[PDB]
Length: 10
Length: 10
Length: 230
Length: 230
Ligand SMILES: Cc1cc(C(=N)N)sc1-c1ccccc1
Ligand SMILES: Cc1cc(C(=N)N)sc1-c1ccccc1
Ligand SMILES: Cc1cc(C(=N)N)sc1-c1ccccc1
Ligand SMILES: Cc1cc(C(=N)N)sc1-c1ccccc1
Image (cartoon, rainbow over all chains, first blue to last red; front, side, top):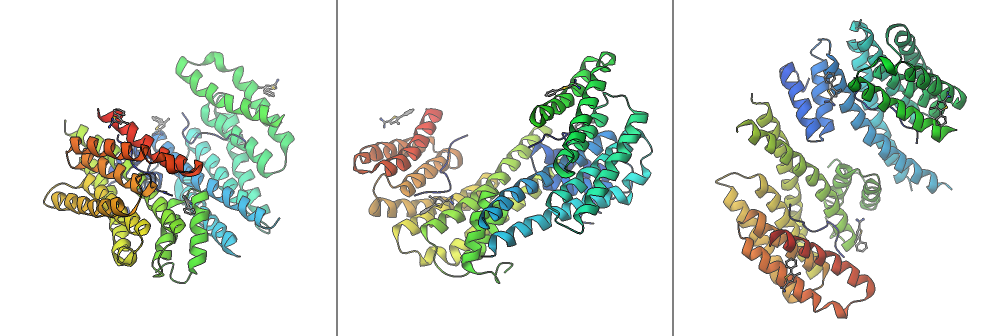
């Protein structure tokens, strides 16, 4: 239920 | 763009 | 046959589980396994087969369309063509697999109108999907194979099923799409959709609440297409 | 190696095409092929790798959760367990494949903070995914492997990157999820998310418009979790 990081990071 | 039949038909 | 060692009932149960998990490639393999047991399929089981493969081929058709678009843009390196060809080839194999199941031996053992029409419709559908990516020498013969399957299914459905039967309705819907999208016959597409819709409307009064909902759902798709096409 | 005969550049181009077509299993195979060429990855290429595998494992985790739920309901025939085990096993192989790429030899060749932190974060993420389905004797050691990867990445990021760096932020976010969801340490999860958010906020004034948007996007995820957790 907890949000994790998008795959793509700038 | 045209709609076709759902897979499941009763 | 991958699935040859699993019980038919377990294959069907796992097909239902994969549907819940949205694992349609698994669902298809399970239902292919069930079909290859050699027994006829119940109405529920035919619907599981159709759902599984329609979702698998549906993702492939969507991918193919994205890639074909890029490829056409690119001619307005071989990679785009190569990768569109890879997806296209995987789509054609899925279509060939379904057609093989219908031909070996679902259609020839289907005696009831509901089963035989369902399978002949599916045959038309999967030749239509092959037609969508076909380009020449075979494109005409593939189109003719879809038309022939659809036409046999229509003839049976008109003799044996009421105009509101959802299988009859989904058949007529897809044949009309075939006419519009594949056969360059938009007038036939529109005529069939109208005639199909009007004859079902005049038979709705005979249905129960739940059957009414089933039929009107497909009728709305016919109406949506008529709005798009006219 | 399936992809050993294809040029590195073509693999990268086809990875980008598969992303557009939402063909993430293909995208992953292409990027695995690119990695196995043995050259370090650019920032864009590391993001392609991450996107591909995160989508593949994401569909497997969602399927696994559906099935585990049904299985738990069923104990409140062996098929549900058998099929959950099949999905679980395919998830573990994907995680093992990614971990193998990081270990052979992406991490050891990554000298810059942006690459080394990115890869160590990924290592933590894929052990966390293994932890989500692990049950005993290995569950503790898997958890400890995720923690260790995350902790090394945090130490580097705090020394080498500003508090608003999106990689540093995505790292801290996922470590906090690890603490809450895997390690039964909700207080650590909440503390880390708060400290991470507050130190980034105090560094936002140094950013351009486009960098500000990148950082605040991840900060919002930290805030969403704090709202969920408190
Ligand atoms: C309409 C339908 C859809 C199904 C599905 N997607 N799992 S199974 C099914 C059916 C058909 C006939 C009798 C009982 C159930
Ligand atoms: C449903 C329906 C029935 C028609 C008829 N044969 N009278 S025309 C039609 C339609 C036409 C264009 C757009 C939407 C609906
Ligand atoms: C942020 C991002 C996302 C990407 C993707 N999903 N294809 S590629 C990428 C990137 C990273 C660094 C430099 C140029 C592009
Ligand atoms: C973003 C943020 C910063 C906080 C702080 N260290 N003062 S508390 C907090 C928060 C807490 C609960 C729900 C949503 C946000």
